[PDB]
Structures are given as structure tokens and as C-alpha cells.
Amino acid sequence: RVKMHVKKGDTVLVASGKYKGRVGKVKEVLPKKYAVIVEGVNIVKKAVRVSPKYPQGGFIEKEAPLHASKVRPICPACGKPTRVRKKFLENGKKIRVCAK
Amino acid sequence: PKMKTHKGAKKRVKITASGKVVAMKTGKRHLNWQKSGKEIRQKGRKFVLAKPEAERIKLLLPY
Amino acid sequence: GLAMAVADRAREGKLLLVEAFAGVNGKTKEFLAWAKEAGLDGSESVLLVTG
RNA sequence: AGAUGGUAAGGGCCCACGGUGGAUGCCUCGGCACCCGAGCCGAUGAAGGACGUGGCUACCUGCGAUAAGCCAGGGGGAGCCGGUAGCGGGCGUGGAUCCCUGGAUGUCCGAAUGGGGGAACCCGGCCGGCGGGAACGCCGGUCACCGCGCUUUUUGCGCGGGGGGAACCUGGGGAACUGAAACAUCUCAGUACCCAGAGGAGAGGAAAGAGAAAUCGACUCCCUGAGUAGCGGCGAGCGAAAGGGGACCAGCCUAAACCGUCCGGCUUGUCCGGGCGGGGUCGUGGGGCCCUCGGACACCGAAUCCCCAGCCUAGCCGAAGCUGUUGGGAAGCAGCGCCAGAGAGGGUGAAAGCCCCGUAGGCGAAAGGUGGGGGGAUAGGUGAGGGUACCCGAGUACCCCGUGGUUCGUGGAGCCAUGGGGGAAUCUGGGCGGACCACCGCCUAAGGCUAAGUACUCCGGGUGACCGAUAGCGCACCAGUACCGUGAGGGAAAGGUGAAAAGAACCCCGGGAGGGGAGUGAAAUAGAGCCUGAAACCGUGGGCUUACAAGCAGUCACGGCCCCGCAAGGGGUUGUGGCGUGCCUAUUGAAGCAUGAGCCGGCGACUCACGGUCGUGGGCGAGCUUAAGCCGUUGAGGCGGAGGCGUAGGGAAACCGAG
Ligand SMILES: [Mg+2]
Ligand SMILES: [Mg+2]
Ligand SMILES: [Mg+2]
Ligand SMILES: [Mg+2]
Ligand SMILES: [Mg+2]
Ligand SMILES: [Mg+2]
Ligand SMILES: [Mg+2]
Ligand SMILES: [Mg+2]
Ligand SMILES: [Mg+2]
Ligand SMILES: [Mg+2]
Ligand SMILES: [Mg+2]
Ligand SMILES: [Mg+2]
Ligand SMILES: [Mg+2]
Ligand SMILES: [Mg+2]
Ligand SMILES: [Mg+2]
Ligand SMILES: [Mg+2]
Ligand SMILES: [Mg+2]
Ligand SMILES: [Mg+2]
Ligand SMILES: [Mg+2]
Ligand SMILES: [Mg+2]
Ligand SMILES: [Mg+2]
Ligand SMILES: [Mg+2]
Ligand SMILES: [Mg+2]
Ligand SMILES: [Mg+2]
Ligand SMILES: [Mg+2]
Ligand SMILES: [Mg+2]
Ligand SMILES: [Mg+2]
Ligand SMILES: [Mg+2]
Ligand SMILES: [Mg+2]
Ligand SMILES: [Mg+2]
Ligand SMILES: [Mg+2]
């Protein structure tokens, strides 16, 4: 509980470091470690694979998780905090001064 | 906590208004049999002390 | 000590006896503006005593 | 004939570099302390356990054969199938996972309770079901004991009890060391411990009180009274009360006389007794019965019950920034802005009010727990005068013998309690006011209940001139564990890679281990019990040095050799000469053949509380100062003269007083 945070799975900007300013859709969000997967931080893994099954695994430089605080949501206007407004029924969330 | 006044000493010694201690003359109750009228009279009056005066002060302090 | 302290700060010439308070409500902007015209640029710590 | 460089099997000193080892620094989920909140659980089976449960499960956690969980009501709004990745297979906006409330299931042990028992095992009776099911086995329900009321009897029916709890609480028992510089009375102490009981508290409690005021007015706790009164082998020591000031505030039911009634007993009566109802509850004495009053409408009003506010048990909203600049990484530096009832704190690759979480401020409950805070109802309760003299708590008061409590140790020894013996009275009664008498005066025993103020902290929260892994709880880490004991019981060590695992693919030596490349990284003497890495201790390389030498190992001088500097000079080494009895403790005296220390590193010893005494800084000064506590605050101060020290001493005291 309360583990919830900023954004979810959608468009997001990154003001981190090695990939500052960059932008991309957040494909994953692990709340336990409080970090999300985007398209910025991507490091090369040399390991063949931990599991013997499927001989080749990949020297892949896949996406590495990223602290969910360095990433910020976005809309028509670039980079905005998050306000919330209970709809005429539900509970949607509006940006700095616009909808959704 | 709270120094207890030495009752054994108060019942037998009163301090002067100044700072001196006074008590009755010793030897006058038992040894008696037929001593010179001087002795018995000399023993009638109280007296001052010296160093141990300070000692007995440190008892009747709250008093 | 209390009076002496007050008398000290006053002797230096800092004990101001205000009364006018354009600060209608609990809004910092108002005070910051009131203090600005009060001669309080913020370059000095102050003990704002008031009821 | 003479003279004097070289030589190192090894050793020494110094310098560089590594190994070992884990000090120091910094870090902190943990711990400590205080404050506030909250406070019982159990035969509807508790506390605490055993066994079992995941597709693959060793342990922890969760759960209980429906066994990482099932049903429903809320909360929440994208992810989820615990720590836990991987093989393998799924769930989620038709709103899951998670959190809060209720419910269901809940093996076997355990108060354990059908019986037995070496706890988690073994064996049954009664009813009903299952398998062909009479022998066998399984499943559901049920059967322990004790207490009280019902049951006329027997047997049954119902209600309760049992056990657990860190500390606190009451009652029944109850030490010794130690102090007294011995010891025996005393002290330690009614403490430790044992035992039974009670619940968020317990106890105590509406005067047979206190004690001298022709006064106060239950009880409990805090100031004070006071180290006073007293106690005491008058030794060591022990140690009240009244009164004043505060918190809190609360007062009630019954026994008896007397009336009705039901039951059974007999010596049959106008009665004895038991059960129930009415009546009655007092110390200006009260009540009963009869008479008179008009004696009814109101007046009092719960501690019990009903509704509600509020509160705990999940949560939600929530102001304000963007580009440059150095870097592995901005939040640092710069430039130009903004919010603030929010500039507390935490995180984000480093140093952030405006990035994330928050904070100020303000929202929220279907359900469950609390709730006189507010309101409502019910119980119960309210008067006068005269007469009558009926009643007012029994092996009790009272007295004596033995004793405990109290400040009271037999003291002149009362009072409160009571093991033994004797043993009354009912207001012309009876206790007490410190032996006794008298007078004056307080109070109504021998029946019970009563909130609050008070104590404690297993549990939750907040805070800290509290610790920071040899500290802090014994335990920051799967610790009451490993290990040690037959058993009570004893009881450790052990934390840190990095911003991210990007945890080093692939080649080479090798059996492996471990290395050398390469690669990741800002960093690899950050490379895996891996941050910082001190010291003892081990080792290689280099400078100087030593095989005719005698010693607390050093110091003083000269010289040679090696190294830094423009020079003079400074550093390392030691050839020769001079001089020289280690440290500590204990002692009249130690180099001592007196004690202690193998070496390094870390933990380790004059504190605090209250009271006293002198000095001292500072405020006030015949005055000075407040204590509990109330108000305020949320790291604010203020009020509060009850009380204490001082202004007069002297005497044993009556008393007198600059004497
Ligand atoms: Mg004479
Ligand atoms: Mg005094
Ligand atoms: Mg080397
Ligand atoms: Mg259980
Ligand atoms: Mg299995
Ligand atoms: Mg698992
Ligand atoms: Mg019958
Ligand atoms: Mg002894
Ligand atoms: Mg002895
Ligand atoms: Mg005693
Ligand atoms: Mg009580
Ligand atoms: Mg109090
Ligand atoms: Mg007291
Ligand atoms: Mg004592
Ligand atoms: Mg009655
Ligand atoms: Mg009545
Ligand atoms: Mg006595
Ligand atoms: Mg008796
Ligand atoms: Mg009574
Ligand atoms: Mg009570
Ligand atoms: Mg510290
Ligand atoms: Mg053994
Ligand atoms: Mg390093
Ligand atoms: Mg030299
Ligand atoms: Mg020694
Ligand atoms: Mg000797
Ligand atoms: Mg000496
Ligand atoms: Mg020696
Ligand atoms: Mg010796
Ligand atoms: Mg030795
Ligand atoms: Mg002192």
C-alpha cells in the first residue's frame, strides 16, 4: 500500500543524467524498487545467460531500470508536475494547467 | 537524602547563638560520694569546646 | 534580563513599535510587501511579536 | 719486513612495495530514555507449540486438509502470483495484487476436559452417515471435574469456574548477607523470594474519624508540615499525624422492630423457623407502631439502559522553475523568475522551499471497537407535632493472658486488629479524646457497594546537548538461536560492492582453485564477507652496515659511504672514542635473582541525586524565595506565598526579655 507513485505506462521525459532531457514511452514500472523502465538507461550485459536452457542468451544491451523520481510525465506542453481532479464521477488526473 | 539530625547529640548539646557549642560538665552523676564543694559546683556549669565543636555542628545542622 | 534585552535592542535603535498591518489575512505576500515598506528588506533577522 | 680496501652463510637500521589483519572515519532497518495514547485474552478452546501446506520449496514469513489462502463490505486505481531470482504456467480497467472491518475453515498438543499417557501419541461408550459392510476402518455430533439456582427423589436442564499476562495492585506467608566498624535486642525489611486473587487498574472509602481550634468533615494521590513530634542495646539508626496548599469530587443499598404471604414441623398454637414481597437506614440521633396534619399534584435523579457528537481501526487533497555551466552524476557555480497558513524532515548518481515523498492547512467510514461529552427514559429518593419506649447488626462490646500494626523495642502505653478464657446492654444504650477518675466534648462498632484523581508499560505513536556494530536491548544479520549442561539454567560471534549488476561474455595456464588478457564502471590495490584499511606480524627489491668481539642497546663527538640543495646546510646508515643499573608497583631501600606486563589494536575506573559546609559570580535586601499545581506553548513564559531561611536571646521547663 502507498507504494503508488508518479506516472504509469505512457509518455515520459527523463531528467536523470547519462540520458538527461531524453523522452520515451515507459514500458515497465516496478514499484518494489521504486523504479521504471524507459528507453534511456540501457547497459550492455556480457553474460551468456543464468539458465542453461536456450544456449544463446544475448550480449544484449537491453533497458536497465531507472529511479522513478528522475522521470517526469508530459503532455502537449513538455514536462509537467501532476495535479488531480475528481471527475463528474470518477477520478482522473490533470497536468500542471491542462487535462490528463 | 535530607541529613538526619543526630538525636543522640541534640538531646545533650545546645549551640550558642553565635556559633559555639555548649554542654554540661562531665562526671557529676555517678563518681560522686563526697567530693569537695568546689568540684560539685565546678561541675554545675556548662562550657565551650574546641575543634570537635565543628564536628557536632555538622549534626544539628537542620536544627 | 527581559527588560534589559529589550532596552538593549532599543538602545541600538531597532525596537520598532508597529501598529499598522495591511496584512489582512494569512498570506506571506502581504507581509513581505508590508515589511518592505516597513523598512524590512530581510537583511536582518527579526522577532515579530504580535497578538 | 710493515701497512690496510674487499668479502655476507646470515643478522641489524632506514626507504619503497605487497600479504595478513580489521582499528579509525562515515553510514543505520536496530536499541535506549522520556512523554502521550491504549490496556486484558481464554471451554464459541487462550497464551505458547508440534506436524503439515507452494507445480518444482531448505529455511523465514503467511496459512490450516477449503491449508501464500475462501466469502462479503469498504479503501485504493496498475500492476500482481510473499523474502525469491530461475525452470514452468497464469491473473488484472467486467477493476486484481495489496490495506481496514466482519465472516468461514481452523489437523494434533496444550487449562485439555470421554479414558490413558513418556505434550503433539494410544484406546473407547452413545446417536447418525459412508464402504458389500455384522466383525474392520473412517466422518460429523456428543460424554471431564468443581461451584451455585432449578430438579421434591433419582437422573437431567441452565448459568459460572479452571488456564495465560512485561510491570503495576491487594491478601496469606517471609529470609540472610550487610549496618551496628565484634554481636545477641535493633538494622537490612515486611525488602528478596514463595503463594492465592483482582483488572485496566488495584486498594481505600461516607467516621463508634481526627484532636483542642466552644474548629475541620469519606477515601486516594502530589506540595508542605519535617528530619519536627517522638522511637531507640537513647547505639547504629528508625520515623509519623493534625493543619495549610493542590488534583479529583459521590454518594448509596441492606439487618433489626412492624404488616402480608408461601412452605413443613410440632408439644396443633393468636407459633417456631426458613424463602419472597412491603416497610427501614440515622448522630441537629434515626426508624417502627397509634393519633393529629390535607397530604396528593411537583421537586431530586442515576454509577443502569437508549440515541447521538466526538475518537481509534484503511485512506485523500495538497502552492511554487527553466536554461546555461563543471562533472561519471547537479540539487554545486551562474543568469533570469516563482510559491509560502507549506523554509520540519527524507530521497533523487553530489550540496533542492519550487524534481519525487512530504510538511502547513483541510477532507473521510458501509462495518467493527469506544463514548453521559450531549439529550432522553427508568430505578430510587423528599415534610411536621404529640404520645407509646418496640428496634438500631454477638461469643461481638467489655475485661484479663499472649501478640501484630502505629513514631511507639513494656515504657506511665492508650488507640486499630485478635489466638485463649470469662462475657453484657439498645439511646438513662455503647466507643473514643494516650494508664486511672471526674468534668467538658467528638462519634455511633460488631452487614455490603461506590466513579474520578493514583501506579505500571507487553502493545502503538511522538520527541531526544542518547548509542552508532567491543556502543546501543543478550540479539541492527532467520538469537534465546549455534554451542554448553542430566537438569533448572547458561549463552556467543556475525552489518556496509556500486549511482546501477552493468557481478567480468570470449581467449590463454590449470584437474580444480586461482591467475593473466579483454570487457563494464567515474573508480576493479571498489571484483564479491568486496567502502575507509591504522598496528602488531610475514615477505621481496634497494641504500648503508657487520665475522678480535663484552651488552637496558641508547646518547654525545669525529670520520667514511648513500641520498636531497646554487651554497652553507639538512636526512639515512654506523666505524671509533666518552658516558650509561629497563618501565610499573611496593618500599627504609629495586637494575634487581621482589610484583605485573609475549606484541598491537579497542572497552576500562572519582559520577549523579538529594541534603550539608566553605568559597565564588549575580539578582534583590529587612527582607529574600516559592513547592505541588493551574493557564499558555508545542523546545515560551506567566500565575501560584501554602511553606521555608532571616529579623532575640536565655533557661531543663514555667517564664522573662536587650537581656
Ligand atoms: Mg549549685
Ligand atoms: Mg526547621
Ligand atoms: Mg609490488
Ligand atoms: Mg492459536
Ligand atoms: Mg511436495
Ligand atoms: Mg516464493
Ligand atoms: Mg421431573
Ligand atoms: Mg552475621
Ligand atoms: Mg563477625
Ligand atoms: Mg522496621
Ligand atoms: Mg477503583
Ligand atoms: Mg499529579
Ligand atoms: Mg510527606
Ligand atoms: Mg531508610
Ligand atoms: Mg427488604
Ligand atoms: Mg424501596
Ligand atoms: Mg503496644
Ligand atoms: Mg479474642
Ligand atoms: Mg453500618
Ligand atoms: Mg473499587
Ligand atoms: Mg554520536
Ligand atoms: Mg551435551
Ligand atoms: Mg575504492
Ligand atoms: Mg650524519
Ligand atoms: Mg605492577
Ligand atoms: Mg617488602
Ligand atoms: Mg615512601
Ligand atoms: Mg621484575
Ligand atoms: Mg608481594
Ligand atoms: Mg611472569
Ligand atoms: Mg551539593
Image: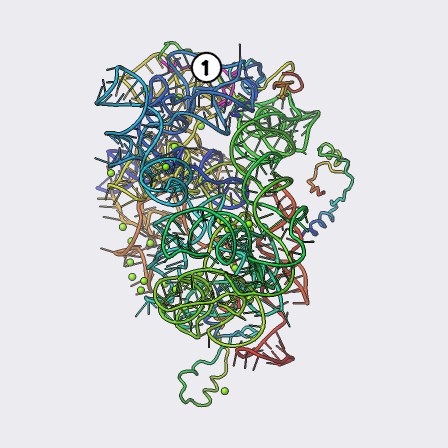
Residue at figure coordinates x 46%, y 90% from the top left:
B37
Residue D230 drawn above or below residue D569: below
Residue A21 drawn above or below residue D359: above
The chain containing the residue under callout 1 comes to A
Residue position for label 1: A44
Residue A30 painted magenta: yes
Nearest the eye: D53 or A60: D53
Residue at figure coordinates x 74%, y 38% from the top left:
C40
Nearest the eye: D651 or C27: D651
Kindly indicate the quadrant of the structure image that contains residue D599. top left
Q: Residues within 10 Å of mark 1 (few under 14, many from 20)?
A: few
Q: Which residues are magenta?
A: A29-51
Q: Is residue B58 visible?
A: no
Residue at figure coordinates x 48%, y 84% from the top left:
B44
Residue A37 painted magenta: yes
Tell me where residue A38 appears, x and y as whole percent: 53, 15
Q: Is residue B5 visible?
A: yes
Tell me where residue D29 appears, x and y as whole percent: 47, 33
Q: Main secondary structure of the magenta part?
A: loop
For residue D657, side relative to residue D583 (left or right): right
Q: Is mark 1 within 8 Å of ligand 23?
A: no
Tell me where residue D654 appears, x and y as whole percent: 57, 79
Tell me where residue A6 appears, x and y as whole percent: 57, 21
Kindly indicate the quadrant of the structure image that contains residue D476. top left
Nearest the eye: D598 or D436: D436
Label 1, secondary structure: give it.
loop
Kindly indicate the quadrant of the structure image that contains residue C21. top right
- Please name the amino acid that badge 1 sits on: Val
Colour scheme of the rendered structure: rainbow
Tally of numbered discs: 1
Nearest the eye: D527 or D658: D658
